Length: 141
Length: 141
Length: 161
Length: 161
Ligand SMILES: *[C@@H]1O[C@H](CO)[C@@H](O[C@@H]2O[C@H](CO)[C@@H](O[C@@H]3O[C@H](CO)[C@@H](O)[C@H](O)[C@@H]3O)[C@H](O)[C@H]2NC(C)=O)[C@H](O)[C@H]1NC(C)=O
Ligand SMILES: *[C@@H]1O[C@H](CO)[C@@H](O)[C@H](O)[C@H]1NC(C)=O
Ligand SMILES: *[C@@H]1O[C@H](CO)[C@@H](O)[C@H](O)[C@H]1NC(C)=O
Ligand SMILES: *[C@@H]1O[C@H](CO)[C@@H](O)[C@H](O)[C@H]1NC(C)=O
Image 1 (tube, chains in turn blue, red, brown, green):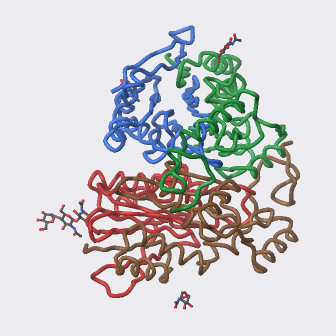
Image 2 (cartoon, chains in turn red, blue, brown, purple):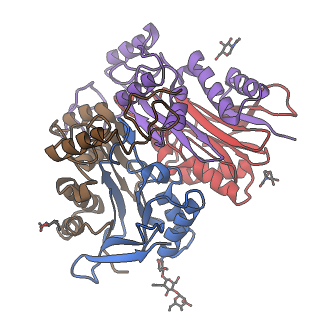
Image 3 (cartoon, each protein chain N blue to C red):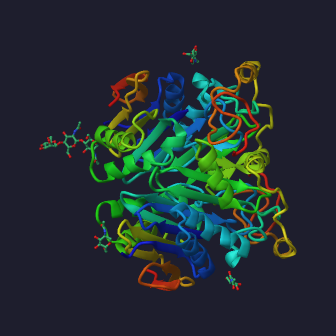
């Protein structure tokens, strides 16, 4: 899955995803990617977020909408993103998931649930300061 | 569309919906009903909510999830439901939609968007306090 | 304030009664929600639930339903379910027999048949008329936009200009 | 200013690049998102995006995609898209040419064809191979539970207990 958040220079935000799902999914299965608020969410008044991981689970917690909701109240992108991971973590401690957050001014962050097999999450960034697609990285909590 | 919320005697909560969609919808269209947080949402730690109306618009604001989110914060069921309608209202003043709310202790409420053709919303309630399902109504805001 | 509590959209009293009856017999909240909603699928509540209603552009009635367990926060759902009347029944089977959350279209039908559901036409003479009257009316209303011919005047096929 | 900004999941740099390029050419935020995601569909990023990957139980690759406009809060989305490669391209068309949010299955394939997309098999020798080794390992892993025969040891079809 690929989740992407883009903030135009004007301040207009857009978000999106594309995926082929999970291997050997039951015929007709649809994950979180095409679901607004789960796979991705964008609002010019707050910010945008995109999620990736086990959509069967993420879908039930609407991670992208909640991340944007936190940012709506002034929360820092990384914090809004970690808080989202923490709530799911309370229900499914072994869930595979990563979320990227960005507020209306251009600040970004990310978070992922730490598994023995998943300890760090990389994501690409590109803005004015960085004149090259910069691969960021975060340790899972 | 029918959206239903039930709180078992043991405090366990469940919610669900069923619908045939909107008349003359494009072949293959899916509304808010089967989407968690949109058509319905249930959480034993917060409460539950269910929505109905124009699913195309509703699913973009995740009404059931946000209503439950407010009650999680302490909001009275009615106020949680009203706040949800307002948020959407600012984006689509003429959208058709109604939401039912209920917190963990059995308090319920509802709200709807006021239209020339829709000024009241009727919903069924069945309490132990009542010995028959009674029809409740709320004036839309 | 006292429990159990059953709340549902619209004055669909029979669904309320059906859900309450399930709880009264010892059924869980999931049993209650399923019973109440299945009642409206059968009674075709307001023609906006179950078969024989809201035909799409091709005249086919497709159902959407979901059921959520508030304890585990497990969910079972189907969208664009074709040729199966008990939509919320199939949704519950998704919850109990898979680790997935949503199954759609003709693929969900196959799944439903595997779970014991009867594959049958969802049309009725009433929904067939509604569709033909709609066609005669130049397909009004519809949800297309930015296409030709003018969707506010004509039927499709449509295409971007 | 720190804007414009492009952020995407995983080390998919070519997708980030296509998105930036879209912006540089005076493209909108939406144009950028579509460009970035489509780039991974062509490239089959990690085999988790685009055709020729993640075959389902039947060996078929089906795609899901979404695009959202933060300004209007309009959303175009497709789920269980069959036989169409440019999933996010189709999702954007749902946004631009209908007032609906989500279209699914073979029905969505028909919609895509109307919008000018090419109908084609999404399988490749690689994905088939992936599927065959799966059949060989007795369909392990799978997402079924509480069915007969035991999903943890055997392949399907399954029936309720
Ligand atoms: C579920 O929703 C209901 C209705 O909003 C909540 O009930 C209200 O709870 C508050 C206590 O938090 C009650 O007000 C307090 O009432 C006592 C009465 O002795 C008074 O001493 C306090 O100064 C204050 O007024 C209020 O009466 C009660 N309302 C109703 C209609 O019952 C309930 O708390 C919610 N449950 C949860 C878990 O959030
Ligand atoms: C965006 O994030 C930064 C870092 O937390 C914060 O200082 C800034 O005020 C945020 N912008 C808004 C509008 O909240
Ligand atoms: C269910 O609803 C219809 C309309 O109110 C009514 O005619 C019917 O008798 C009700 N069901 C039963 C079992 O009475
Ligand atoms: C872009 O990334 C892919 C991996 O997804 C790599 O194989 C390819 O060489 C890169 N594109 C170009 C034009 O070099």
